[PDB]
Length: 276
Length: 288
Ligand SMILES: COc1ccc2c(c1)cc(CNC(=O)c1cc3ccccc3o1)n2CC(=O)O
Ligand SMILES: COc1ccc2c(c1)cc(CNC(=O)c1cc3ccccc3o1)n2CC(=O)O
Image (cartoon, rainbow over all chains, first blue to last red; front, side, top):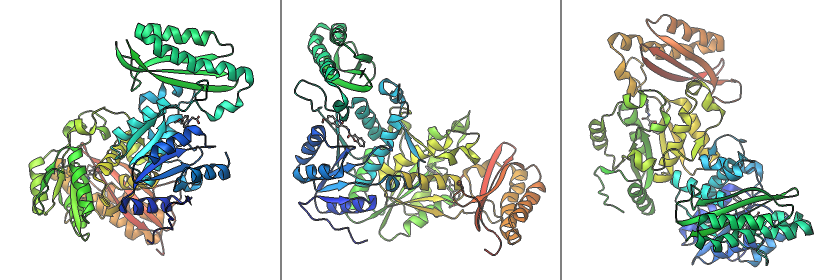
């Protein structure tokens, strides 16, 4: 019942859930507002944008979890976080996260069966289960996700509302390459022809977002034409929904989402759309 | 913060109100105890409340909510006893300071959407014929725990499979609460307390003593091993007028995927007319 060592203003690494839970609770008692940034593999600028967002809350202490599925290299990742002034990295093993194996889990609502839930019908159960655990271990005031995985973000908001969780969910605008391609660990697999064609996803969506003054059908036809101008872009879906991913209403706010396969690589993108 | 009057019973229906009060209290040093109930309070519930009040510095929150999601049927949901007036009167007499009495709309404003899927235990025993019953229980318990954020949550051992699943929920989702299991309160003859005992007619009430008789006979027979324990309990249930046994199972204490060693739980469920009764007891095998 002694609190684990915490050195303020340094990067403190913990692998044990109980240690990070004790430190986060001790920190919340001393004033600090605990921010959580969940991550998975090699850190990229997308991830750094979540960190920076969390850093700007006055009195924040930022916790970055690094944990691979059951849903890169440790050296550089940790160097990057130190550089960002992150004070806690949580790096648990699979065994420490799942000491009893897979047992009680979260069952998403029917949204999880749609869109990405078509090829990966249990994917979102995994993500929601591990999010719930990280939220209970760290007990942050705010948790930060990219808007890139939009359906994921919406399901997370559903989790927080449905299970009455305390935490504020912050969606952070997707970081993009110079030509608009949304950042993703998958981008590096693309060969040159594929990387050149992949700019069609973001170009389609931004075209649709500007075509939308002319109504929903013009937005969708614009995105579709841009996708049709690209070779080797196999479109899995292109759907305009309302902001919670229900059916898009006659006018007002929506989201347009696309997924496509370029060779063996699946890419996704989405954008805010205002109808008329 | 709504009003909170200490040494009185404060009743809140809105989850935001009880959440605000509970947080406010924990931050002034009071430890928050939660006793979840479905109302129709009996002495077994008052044992939970007493256990909670005995924790130094406690404030006791008792929830009363008949959770539609854990009911199947049928007319089971509409049939559950509701005695709101006797319930709050009991809580005032026990010196409880908070009752949380949410509406169905406040708990399920989006209907059934994200839910808890229990592990494989939920498909065994009570769950075999009621495959979504324990997903409903665990989903509600998770919500009540997030709304109230108690330090310690109290459950009877009578619904032992439920208590085991609740400890699984707490371990598997890293919940910060301690689960306290309180031994079943029984009538003078041994009959386990239950909201459903009111549906036994005089003859069924007489015959219902066989469940606890059979279990206590087994716990003592158990020096002679598992088969003798099981056969003692079966003999007693067989001797009982109009008791229809649904199962009698001797399991390891976790009810889980491990064999019985020295410590077991013997569980029984039986029908007296239309009334399903459950009971269970600790069993030590042999030299235990
Ligand atoms: C703000 O700009 C952007 C742009 C693209 C982004 C991100 C941010 C963040 C991500 C990837 N998501 C995670 O690492 C992640 C989510 C998650 C959920 C639960 C547990 C661990 C988790 O880890 N990507 C896309 C990607 O890398 O493919
Ligand atoms: C300490 O001695 C005993 C003996 C028998 C007991 C009890 C105590 C308590 C109960 C009934 N349980 C609830 O009302 C209840 C509500 C609830 C709500 C959410 C999660 C779990 C929940 O459990 N029974 C048995 C019964 O009444 O059939």
